[PDB]
Amino acid sequence: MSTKAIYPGTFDPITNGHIDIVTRAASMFDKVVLAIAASPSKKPMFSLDERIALAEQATAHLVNVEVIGFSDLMANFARAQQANILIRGLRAVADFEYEMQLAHMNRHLMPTLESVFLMPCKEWSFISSSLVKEVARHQGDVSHFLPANVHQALLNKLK
Amino acid sequence: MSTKAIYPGTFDPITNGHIDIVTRAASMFDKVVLAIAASPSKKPMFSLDERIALAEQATAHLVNVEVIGFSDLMANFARAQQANILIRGLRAVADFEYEMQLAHMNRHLMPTLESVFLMPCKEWSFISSSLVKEVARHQGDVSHFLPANVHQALLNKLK
Image (cartoon, rainbow over all chains, first blue to last red; front, side):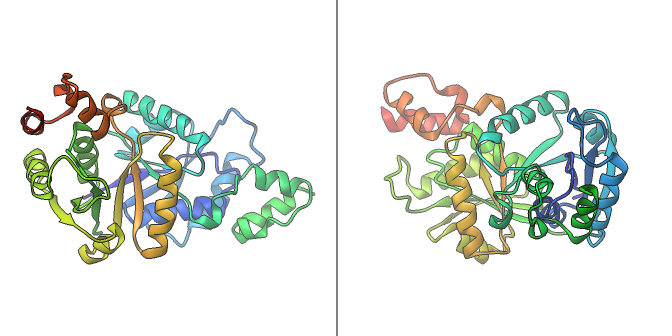
């Protein structure tokens, strides 16, 4: 009943793994905002506008998904968006501790916000989006891991 | 716009941690079945009928939650119940690998079934049916961890 979720991340760039997560989120909640962090601590390969553009194209086929940049705490953005659900992808064990921490902090910041964890398809279990960049930087075939539009934009960035 | 989840487990017995998980599940999905495994491999302290009774009482305040026994694979029961969502409590990093395995198997058995992972409230982050029972078996105060009705039943089982 009127479920609204945010799916925050850097999405530098968005990968088939992300698409899978947001697709499955969009299948179980009424609305999903794919929230792109504006000022990440790490210098991203793509600008906020570029990242939004690529994500938009890659998720245009999802009716109930909307891309939006944000610069605040993901907890504050969720409050502004009147989201009661926070989507987090769970790839590996190492990340689990951090994700527990973040959920407990987010509970502290906004107790009505519910963190929800999804695992990726086996296909995308071992892709990193930093391993994808790194492989691409040193001239490898990453076509299987990215949406066509994203792959093109990445090829251009390495010239 | 329609969501039906199962939350499978042995629930021998149901704890505050379980109640917390199913409560949060019930807040974000239209219907939630608290599915109690009939014949766990291990011999449970309480019978299926007892485990149903205690869980019923302890979830009677949740309108859209229904307790049901099952004896098949959780993936088949989900198919029977027309569940598209499977709730898993994800407390320990140790259990994460197993949970990843299970979701991959459950995706094999029923591809339309979406595994969803929730982390407990900090308060219940360290409790298990097993450690509660063990403490209680050697005469310790477990009142904080169990619904009153469950606590009473457990005291009687050990006296």
